[PDB]
Amino acid sequence: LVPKLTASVTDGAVGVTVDAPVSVTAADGVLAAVTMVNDNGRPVAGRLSPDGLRWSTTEQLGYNRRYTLNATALGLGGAATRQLTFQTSSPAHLTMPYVMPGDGEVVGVGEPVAIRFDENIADRGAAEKAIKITTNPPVEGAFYWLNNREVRWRPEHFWKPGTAVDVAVNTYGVDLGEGMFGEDNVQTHFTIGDEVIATADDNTKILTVRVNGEVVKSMPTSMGKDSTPTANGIYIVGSRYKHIIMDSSTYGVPVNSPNGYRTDVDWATQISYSGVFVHSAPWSVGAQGHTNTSHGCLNVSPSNAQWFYDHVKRGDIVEVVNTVGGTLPGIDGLGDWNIPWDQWRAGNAK
Ligand SMILES: *Sc1cc(Cl)c(Cl)cc1C(=O)NCCO
Image (tube, rainbow, N blue to C red):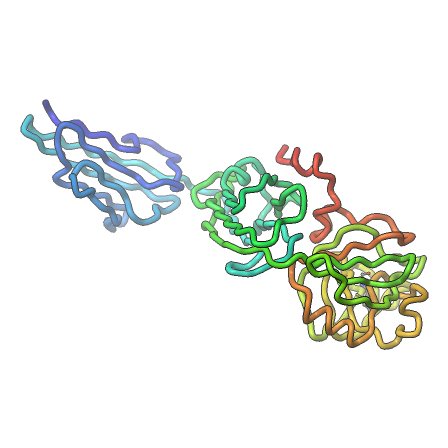
């Protein structure tokens, strides 16, 4: 019985993807020698199994490299040697993924998994296939693309507090379309904290904060005036600022135009990419609880805005109801829950 060799690559292959290790296996014998070098002669790190049967690379293989693999097997039957050479994928472009929320964070019940690429993704299905989301307790979720670069994953309903979420973006070696390959892999983990839902009801002009179902704060508010109203819908809480300059040019609106503005405010909590915040508004305290005066943001008192800053976290929820506005776009960036579940579940990988 002459020993046989079985490699995970074929001699002469090209376009070999680097998303998996390269292996050599011996049958009816054992591996006496296995080496693999790149085109600069640099040895590739590997490991031989204690039983001598299975050898495998132990470091990532490179893009745009030619590798030469030599292997010898020995056995009572005799010996066998093979030499194999192959070339790995040569990307036309690289894209790097960025994942939110941050590793180890505790977030609110409305926080989606977010995978943002720094380039347009031509094969959204390949990107989705490369992303593994683990949930404990397990829950059904689905992917939906907000734009050509960023995909989101969430359940049908708000997360259950206490849920562990693990995200593995294994895009290295993956053809994401049109010669674009993943620049690296990413791996993050987060946990769902307490349920915090704040409701701004235009009929009362009160922003009511509920923690685990209990009213803990009631904030008089002034929202957008009729000509620049606050959109109804579900908003996800994002970033927090002790102070920030609100500049309309950020959104293509010249500061000196009718709806333009440039002002510094305190205690600002972001709730939409379109620039809606909860923030301190000393100048509208008389209107708070009575009339809408803003350009769309939720004006509250300095003390209530700081309380909001101190007690609300990324992924908590603000829901606005009964304004004269429309509904916040589902693809805003923090408007994901406004997409109906059936549409989100069906996705848009194309
Ligand atoms: S959030 C905000 C704060 C202030 Cl002080 C002004 Cl003048 C405008 C805005 C704003 O409208 N941002 C855009 C979202 O409507």
